[PDB]
Image (tube, rainbow over all chains, first blue to last red; front, side, top):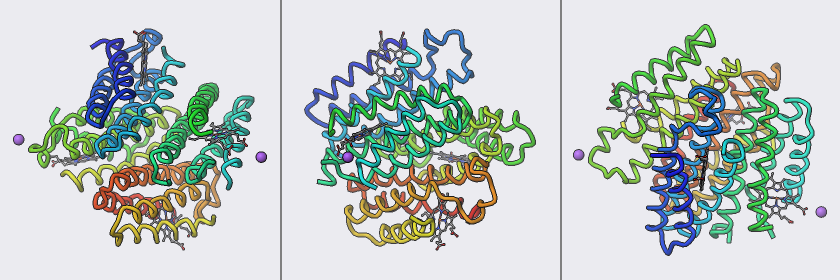
Length: 106
Length: 101
Length: 106
Length: 106
Ligand code: HEC
Ligand code: HEC
Ligand code: HEC
Ligand code: HEC
Ligand code: NA
Ligand code: NA
């Protein structure tokens, strides 16, 4: 799907996690955030249409998602142990990874 | 060392990076920031296995990751790009300050 | 491609890096390993074919590749800066990631 | 602390995890390993005293601790979820990273 649709699925499910009641709701939100981030992996962003797939910048771009996928998995792991407090706070801490890619490429 | 001392090192060296002219200065400072962060990991700010303390420790884990990626750039001589990465660290410094400072 | 084929590629290109005499061999080999690790990420290994796609084991197994893809990219980045020796060394260090996965799921 | 000391901390605490019976022991042992690895990251080993701090050998030396820290972090993740057996098995798999650094630099 589109990068915007993935960025919407990321932004939406983050607020789902913030306002959730339990680990199942958190989990399925993280599972959807994960699938969306791995789907936006291939996208060329508007601000780098003048760079090739194997350029330094597109490696750095794709690496920003590698970081995000990893953190989602750490959070998701916390949800699967029934640690909802901690998972919710881990999800919160993604914000600076989201932010860091935007400060460079959004 | 003490928690104030780790924060000082982190703050001091973030400035050294801001005003640096070369990759060696920037490496040196990132390296010292990595050490202070891989140190401050195991302190308590004003239960150890509480949800708060995990998340306190987790903040330093995330910060260590970003310092290490900045080091990647500085080790590759990409000095400007390392300095921007270093500027973006503030988000994590701040986000933890908002919480538990 | 098949999981076995991804694994030959990984093993073959790892020995190419070991024996390389120039920067292009290491870079090219690291590029082919990155692609093969990415492709293999979604595969289901024989020993977990009767597990759910959302089992803890399939998350662990998927994560093992997340680790590997990360080290491959670290090494590739080093090679792209002319730190080819460091990249060859990094490639050798992959072996414990290869072994960690095999131990559990091969 | 001294490098030998950090190694002594790594070795003793690994043995503690192997023969543990609860999560608290495992978490605490891994925490001493992390701190030992952190502190050891900055050291210069006897065999690389005759090299530049920016040498491939020293870069690769530091990297071995980076890999090890990452594996300790994961083991710590399993231990926090009371997945004691799995954390003990992840701890065992650290020995590959130990051995790989020793074979080169010890
Ligand atoms: C790259 C490494 C990114 C990561 C990781 C995240 N985002 Fe993103 N985002 C990125 C780009 C390049 C863009 C621009 C999209 C475009 O087509 O111009 C975005 C955009 C967004 C948006 C706005 C989408 C829109 O329709 O205007 C949002 C709301 C957004 N991003 C949210 C978001 C969140 C919540 C993330 C992590 C939790 C995240 N992004 C990560 C690049 C990258
Ligand atoms: C937790 C996850 C933290 C991260 C990451 C960073 N900081 Fe920190 N910082 C933290 C706490 C709990 C406190 C309060 C400590 C106290 O006893 O007052 C601080 C404080 C500081 C300070 C002020 C220290 C003082 O003597 O008053 C500074 C200057 C500071 N922190 C800087 C800093 C920088 C530069 C960081 C990242 C680059 C950073 N901190 C991260 C907790 C955490
Ligand atoms: C999971 C997280 C894996 C990682 C990372 C690596 N390997 Fe792998 N490998 C894995 C599985 C499940 C299997 C069994 C495949 C099967 O269908 O039986 C393998 C197999 C191999 C093989 C042998 C293939 C065969 O003919 O039986 C080799 C040579 C191999 N793997 C090499 C290899 C290398 C070099 C890796 C990292 C550098 C590596 N593997 C990582 C699972 C995983
Ligand atoms: C480098 C990247 C290392 C990693 C990772 C590990 N070890 Fe280590 N170890 C390393 C060096 C260079 C040395 C030699 C130190 C010296 O002064 O000679 C060692 C030594 C040890 C020792 C011997 C202690 C002594 O008194 O000399 C032990 C017991 C030891 N190392 C244990 C150990 C363990 C358990 C690790 C993982 C579990 C490990 N090491 C990783 C370098 C590195
Ligand atoms: Na003071
Ligand atoms: Na089946």
